[PDB]
Amino acid sequence: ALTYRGADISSLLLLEDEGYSYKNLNGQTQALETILADAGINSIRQRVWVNPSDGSYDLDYNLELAKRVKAAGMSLYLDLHLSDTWADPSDQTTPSGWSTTDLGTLKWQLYNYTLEVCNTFAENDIDIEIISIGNEIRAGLLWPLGETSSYSNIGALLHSGAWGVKDSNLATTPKIMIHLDDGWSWDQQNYFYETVLATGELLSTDFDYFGVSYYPFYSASATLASLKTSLANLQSTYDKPVVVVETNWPVSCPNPAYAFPSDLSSIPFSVAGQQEFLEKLAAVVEATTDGLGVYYWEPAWIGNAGLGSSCADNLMVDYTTDEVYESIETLGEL
Ligand SMILES: *[C@@H]1O[C@H](CO)[C@@H](O[C@@H]2O[C@H](CO)[C@@H](O[C@@H]3O[C@H](CO)[C@@H](O)[C@H](O)[C@@H]3O)[C@H](O)[C@H]2NC(C)=O)[C@H](O)[C@H]1NC(C)=O
Ligand SMILES: OC[C@H]1O[C@@H](O[C@@H]2[C@H](O)[C@@H](O)[C@H](O)O[C@@H]2CO)[C@H](O)[C@@H](O)[C@H]1O
Ligand SMILES: [Ca+2]
Ligand SMILES: [Ca+2]
Ligand SMILES: [Ca+2]
Ligand SMILES: [Ca+2]
Image 1 (cartoon, rainbow, N blue to C red):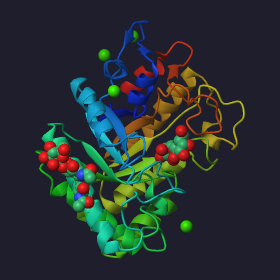
Image 2: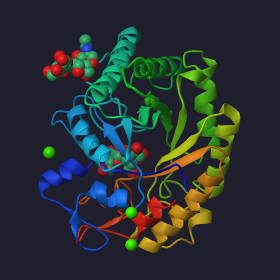
Image 3: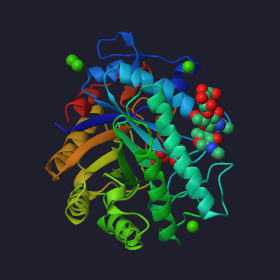
């Protein structure tokens, strides 16, 4: 098995608030984290926002959710969006209150944030396994100061964030991840790290794990073969372990906006499809020297079945009954 077989279920507490509830494989209502834990899912990924208006995905939200993850027996991976809202390669909005004008000041705010996110978690007695300094930061983070016009700035902000983690009172220090999208592209992956490390503002010893996203429905170049190479090259070149931290496969996709990659076009859009996909992905990752795991993105997000894609349903739960699909078991045995 993979060391880590996970899911990001950040939406859970918001969805429980609206009324919703989940059924296990045997038709009995049960808390989603216990259902998942029972399937072999050993790790839960959670997105963190800094000061969202309505408190979605804030620190308090995450402590509430992480207690339940801890209780259930699973490890915790915090995905620091380092923003008040969605962070991705086309939106990296600096948190309100943080500097859009002074790097010296933004670095301090970031150090303080990671330090004290960590110290609060240590205070509430919750262990953190993985913390990412940004979500999908290939186009940088904390705009404008960390836009890709300044890899020197990005490198320096990462160093600040990492150092807040190291300096916290966590009994065990979380493994620090840098997370880029387009995991399949070695040129994208390598370009970021060589350019940033070349500056000398990020040190190789500032972080522990590579994270990558790997989605099949945003470009026909996302071949399993291209991912195998990207992952192997990241590891050979920089001597660090690699994790696929976000992936989906549709159980229904009638109007894709992009051709699926050539080595995945024979996989159906069904629950069985999801399993075959996850198995083929897991094999790539098992065979990568030091390939530690796979996390599915938002398997249970009722009312957002498309999960942002041009595909109709990417969930691992039946949204007509709120019952989890068998694909959850395949995820847990990867
Ligand atoms: C540095 O980072 C923290 C983390 O976001 C910023 O928010 C402040 O966090 C501290 C530490 O958790 C809070 O203080 C603590 O509050 C609890 C409950 O009231 C109390 O039991 C602890 O003993 C401690 O006082 C603080 O309230 C919170 N502040 C805000 C405005 O939310 C902090 O502000 C950052 N620092 C700067 C100077 O920007
Ligand atoms: O509700 C959809 C939501 O998707 C967000 O993006 C997620 C994820 O956070 C990213 O890390 C990844 O690149 O893509 C997925 C969507 O497939 C997005 O940031 C939001 O704007 C929403 O569309
Ligand atoms: Ca609640
Ligand atoms: Ca069974
Ligand atoms: Ca079980
Ligand atoms: Ca730009």
